[PDB]
Every structure is written in structure tokens, then in C-alpha cells.
Amino acid sequence: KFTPPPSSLRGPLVIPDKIMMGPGPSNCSKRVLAALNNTCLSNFHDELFQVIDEVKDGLRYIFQTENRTTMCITGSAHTGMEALLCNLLEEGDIVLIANNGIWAERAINMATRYGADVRVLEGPADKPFSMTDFKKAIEQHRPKCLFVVHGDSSSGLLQPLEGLGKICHDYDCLLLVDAVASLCGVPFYMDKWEIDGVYTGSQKVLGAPPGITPISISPKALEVIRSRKTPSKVFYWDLLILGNYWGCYDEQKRYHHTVPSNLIFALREAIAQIAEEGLEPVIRRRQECAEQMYRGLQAMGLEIFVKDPEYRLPTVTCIMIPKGVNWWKVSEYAMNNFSLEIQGGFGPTMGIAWRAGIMGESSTLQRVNFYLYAFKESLKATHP
Amino acid sequence: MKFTPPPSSLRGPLVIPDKIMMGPGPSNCSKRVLAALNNTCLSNFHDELFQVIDEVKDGLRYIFQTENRTTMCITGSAHTGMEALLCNLLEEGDIVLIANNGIWAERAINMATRYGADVRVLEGPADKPFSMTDFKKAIEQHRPKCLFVVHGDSSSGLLQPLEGLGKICHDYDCLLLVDAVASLCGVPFYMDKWEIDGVYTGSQKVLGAPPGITPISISPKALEVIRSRKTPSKVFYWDLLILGNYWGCYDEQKRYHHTVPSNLIFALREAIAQIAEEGLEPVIRRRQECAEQMYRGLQAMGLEIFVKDPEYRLPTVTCIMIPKGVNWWKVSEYAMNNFSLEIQGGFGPTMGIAWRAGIMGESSTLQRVNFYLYAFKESLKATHP
Ligand SMILES: *Cc1c(COP(=O)(O)O)cnc(C)c1O
Ligand SMILES: *Cc1c(COP(=O)(O)O)cnc(C)c1O
């Protein structure tokens, strides 16, 4: 005797192809999606350990670090933010957060939740912080950790990082960076920029399925986690024990949790494509695409949230909605008529812009010209 | 740009062979379930994804057996189910009782300490379950906010009866929380009938779906406890009041929470559908029957089972006692190299003294059990004459 099954599961799974040029999930390649179609291996199968070691080598490549303490967390990229703050901060520890968009606000939320003394450097969403802004705020607050968003997908803002680590280190402070939307889209040098903790997202520039999160921490950062008098609040992403299974220490592997092998298979292959082509050509192609996007947008009389090109994040461009234009009518027509994802605004850009992403397989000149055409045609047909 | 160069290990191709997965480990997924992964990673606000989501919620209500509006998934492996229940329901200083006769309860003791709880333990041996008396005593003693039970223990091969337990817990104003990872769709389970306040399962165990997405459900009484909380829970990522918002469990406009793993949610949809098609009961009946055969064939090898009373065995995991002077690894190795069969070693209470045989996913067939039994046999003979 059971309550009978619902009728909503009687039909098939039907997902159409979409051209995914939000900042959202990106298009993954054929090679990457085929990698999902494999045995969900055991935690302790040799073939899985092999894939994990290759993935760690690949992450040290795309992060540009020698950090042994390089792994994935099982979850979305939020998970990276959670783990850096959860692990590195005890009750009362002072964290400084540079806030000019919604991802800082998330970080402010979590750090309060883990019981930290949160200090906030506030700024306008459309301009970056100067080294002078950071120095004063570190002097004032004398924080254990600084948290900074590198590429803000909610603004289209790229925060320059050259020298912030030296400054952080002069004041005995760890430097933590979100590189979810920035990595493989612009130059990034974890070690030379003296970053003590970074994470990215599988579904942004890498063009891999969501659900698995690259993370890396510095020897200094490992040392602070080892020093803690109190245990971190979450077993699931305690980096001393997750690190163990990921074979980051001089220890026998122990079962911690069941890793999403299929997702990890897809991530290996995604890194492989970037290694094959080379990190520098991949970044340049994304840079060239963004130039083309700016040229086309200029030709159409449309503006960009971040006015100063120097400080624009190439992978996410926030296109301003002109007076008299309904944004959702454009987005809805594009999807319905071209299968194009033209995503609305978010955080500081809510209500005032669309977000145009150049990530994964949509990082080509041909995809950029189809975006502006479809966008243009979607305006005209919804506003005459 | 002068980047450190890429590693040569990425130069070659990915090669993941087919394996028969009859550990408790991950299971074999059907063709249909794996194919589902191969689809567009959708936006969090695409109608199509919202549709699949509603179908996952309907199908979860089915296999959990509940009308709970607060049914959803956590993005993560099943440990996330244990995290989120303890995390959401326990404030600094609240009192939690944890029935402990296995490694999954040790994990729950580890998590609950970290979250700042007053942890009480009811200890007991791994190879027999708790009486309703045993619970009732423990519940009087400690008068706790929540009790936490493992329904199906993949470390032992033990199944814990639950009929009655709900009404006892509620009498003392205590919530009942259950781990149904290794038991859901393997044995009967009635979330509402049995007055359960919190359950989760795993995608990779009985359902035969890929790991990474974790179904969870909480009662209207549990929801009210969380809303009553005097402090905010410690983890935004699995705060059910806001995760629950995106999954459309509440009378609020949907807000973005996190990027859900659309591909794993699609595979989960299909896995639930496979079970809906044949029907819950036939599916459970087939797995019971498979276990029966497994016991009869183990009996005919003169091998023993950690959990001695059949009335207390979990059919989905059977721990097979290593005979004295038998090298377990030499068996398991030969099983893998000659048959591509996973014969998993022991873990927790059963480490050093068992293999663990699983009847899960697409290996839940007579034909596959009969294959395990044959391959085990040949493996022993060839490595221990
Ligand atoms: C998308 C994004 C996140 C959140 O990651 P999810 O996988 O969506 O949970 C965090 N930080 C930045 C910069 C992002 O672009
Ligand atoms: C395997 C298992 C877990 C752990 O789940 P993961 O998906 O590996 O994180 C928890 N509980 C039970 C009963 C299990 O069998």
C-alpha cells in the first residue's frame, strides 16, 4: 500500500539546445558532456584517483600556484566562499570585506553566520578600489582576513589585484579571492600576486557542468587552519579532512564523502581543452570577443554599466536598459525566436541592465555577432 | 603572459571502464539515467528547469511517502542531508540524542558538536537494533529537542525498525530525524505514517542515479521549529528557509539562491521516474527477493553475515564475514581484474572482518546476484585452494 505516483513523471525528459550567453551556466563542449557518460566510480578506484591527480595538476595550472592544498568541494561555487570563511575564521576573528556588489553581500552574510567580527569597505558598484583604499581600511581594522571579488558577474567590474597581497602580508593578513567569473577569462597568478585562498566555478568560463568547485589555499593559510583551537563548523568542507581524501597531505587517504565522479570527469576534460589550446590564447580569444562586443554595442547606441574599459571584466558585460524599453520582453523574444539566453540584471544592476556573458563554448567571434543580431532584432520586434 | 606550462598528464584521453558496482558504493545507473546528464546546463530561472524541479518534488513526495510541501534537494553528496538537518534544527546549546551503533552516527556526533549542540549518545552494538524501550529510556533521561536514527546502515548491513518511534518522540515534544540513504526504495518507508520530521537520501545508493544531488524533506512541525529559531543557522548554503524559497516550497516570489546542478537533477528525475513506472512495491519486492537469493547462495558457500537475525538485515547491504586466514584483498583484486566486479571491503564496525555486497540500482536483479555469487566463488577458489 502506497500513495500512487504522480502523473507528472509519465512523460519523457525534453531539454532543448539553448545558446547560453548569460553569465549563468555556459555551453559545454561535446567532449565535456560525453565525459558525464561513464561509470559512477567508487571513492577508492585507481582510475578515479588518477583523474583526481590530473585535475589537481590542471587546477594548479589554471590558478597558477604550486599549492599542494588544491582540491574541489562537492557543490556550487557558493561552496568556495563558505569553506574559506568557515575554515579560516574562528568566533571573534576580524574579517575585512571589500563590498561593491552582491557577492560581497553574500560573504558578509556567511561570515556573520560563522560568528566573525565583520568589517566592510564600501564602494560604488561601477568603479574599483585603489591600493590606497585597501591600505587605509587594513590599517584601521587590522583584520585576520581580507575578502575581495575579482570579477563581479553582477556589475561587469574587474578589480585589479597587483600588490594587495604584499600589503595584506605586511599587516599579517591573509588575502582571499573569488575568481568564479574571472578565471581563464583574464590573466591570473595566484602565487605571484600572493593570494592565500581562491575558488572558481565549473559552469562559468570553464564551460563545465555545475556542481563541483575548484579551491586552493597557501601554506600560510593551511598553517592558520592547523592553529585553530576550535574545530571549524562544517565537516563536509573542513579542508584538513577533505584535503586528506584529495591526497593533499602526507597521509593515507580516508573516506570523507562520495565525490561526484561524473562531474569530475567533465571538469578534467574542460581543463584539458584549455591546456591543449593554452591558457594565454584562451584568455586572448575571450579579450578579443569582448572588444567585438563593445564595438557592436557602441554601434547600437547602448551603454555599459562600467564606463571605463580598463576596469571592465571581459567575460560579463552589463548592457544598460534604455528609457522606454521593457527588458523581459527582449529576453523572452530572444529565447522564443533564437534560443538565445539574454539574462536580466542582478544585485547592483537589478532593473537597469542585461548581463551578456562570454564563457565556455560561446567565446567566439561568431557567437558574439549572433548575440548582437538577435539582441537587435529582439528589440525591434518588441518595440516598434 | 609567461604562465607556468600545463601538465603532460592532461595530454592523454579519459578512459573510465565499465564496472559491475555491487559494493554499497555508488551503483550502476540505467542507460536512461546516464543519458539524461547529456543535456543543456539550464539557467536557474528557465521554465524547463522549474518544470523538472516540480516533477522531482512530486516524485520525492512519492518515494519518501509524505505530502510535505517542504521537500527539495541540497546541492552536494548525501553527507549534506545530515549537515542540513542538524544545522537547521539545532541552536547553540539545544539538546540532540543520537542513537549510535555505527560510523554514520559517529559522523552525526562530529557534525552536531561542531554546530555547538549538547550531544547525548545512546550506545549499542553494531549487529542488533534499538528496542522502542531503549529509545523511550534515552528520551526520558536527556529530554532532547531532536532524536537522530540511522534507518539503513551501510557499515553493518543492519536495519532499524521505526514503527512507533515517531509517536514516542512527539509525546516528549521531540523531533525525529532519520538517515534513509541506504534504505529508501530498498524497504518500505512511510514518512508521514511513521511521524518522521526529517529525512534525506542519496542519489547514488538505491535510486541508481549519479552522486551530487541530495533529496531532503521536513514536516510542518520541523519547519515551525526552524522559523522559531532565536539565532540564524550557520550555513547560508543549506538554510532551508532560503534554499526552500528557490525550490518554491513557500508563498514567496522565487529568489536566486545558488546554481543548482541541472544535469544531476535531470538524472535524478529519470531515476525517480523509473521507480514510478514499475511502482514502488514491485521495486521493493524485487530487492527483497534478490537479497533472499544472496543469503541462500552465501549459505551454500558456508559464509556468515555480520547481522545474524534476518528480521533485522538491510537487503541493500550484506556484510560477508571473511573466514579465518583468508586475504580479503586478494579476492577483491582478482574479482576486479578477471570480472570487472566491485567486491568492496569493510568499513567502520565491519573494517577488517567483512566484505560488503550491495543490491542497488541496476544490479538489483536475480541475474546480477547470481553473477556476484559465481564470481565471488571463483575468486576464493583461485586465490585460496
Ligand atoms: C555565479 C557566481 C557565484 C555563485 O556560484 P554558484 O555556482 O552560482 O553558487 C559566486 N561568485 C561569483 C563571482 C559568481 O560569478
Ligand atoms: C554512503 C552513505 C552516506 C554518505 O553519503 P555520501 O553520499 O557518500 O556523502 C550517509 N549515510 C548512509 C546511510 C550511507 O550509506
Image (cartoon, coloured by chain):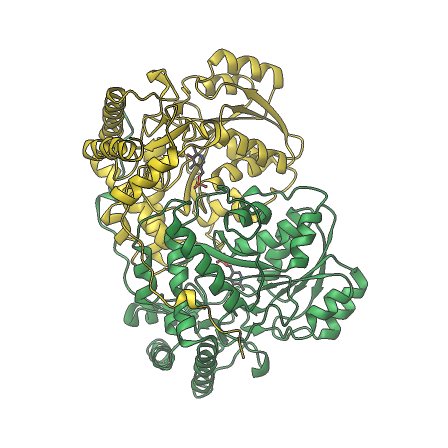
Chain colours: A yellow, B green
What residue is shown at x 42% (from left), y 64% (from top)? Answer: A8
Q: Report the label total.
A: 0
Q: Is residue A339 above or below residue B383?
A: above
What residue is shown at x 47% (from left), y 77% (from top)? Answer: B284
Tell me the quadrant of the picture where the C terminus of chain B can be found: bottom left
Tell me the quadrant of the picture where the N terminus of chain B can be found: top left
Q: Is residue B330 above or below residue B94?
A: below
Left or right of B106 on screen, residue B73: left
Residue A197 is situated, as x and y percent measured from the top left of the image, at 47, 32
Residue A383 is situated, as x and y percent measured from the top left of the image, at 31, 31
Q: Is residue A375 visible?
A: yes
Left or right of B132 on screen, residue A144: left
Residue A243 is situated, as x and y percent measured from the top left of the image, at 47, 44
Q: Residue furthest right?
A: B141
Q: Is residue B272 visible?
A: no
Q: Residue furthest front?
A: A384
What residue is shown at x 67% (from left), y 50% (from top)? Answer: B226
Kindly indicate the quadrant of the structure image that contains residue B180: bottom right
Q: Residue furthest left?
A: A366
Q: Nearer the viewer, residue B341 or B293?
A: B293
Q: Is residue A60 above or below residue B134?
A: above
Residue A194 is situated, as x and y percent measured from the top left of the image, at 44, 24
Q: Nearer the viewer, residue A91 or A8?
A: A8
Q: Is residue B43 above or below residue A11?
A: above
Q: Nearer the viewer, residue B89 or A135?
A: B89
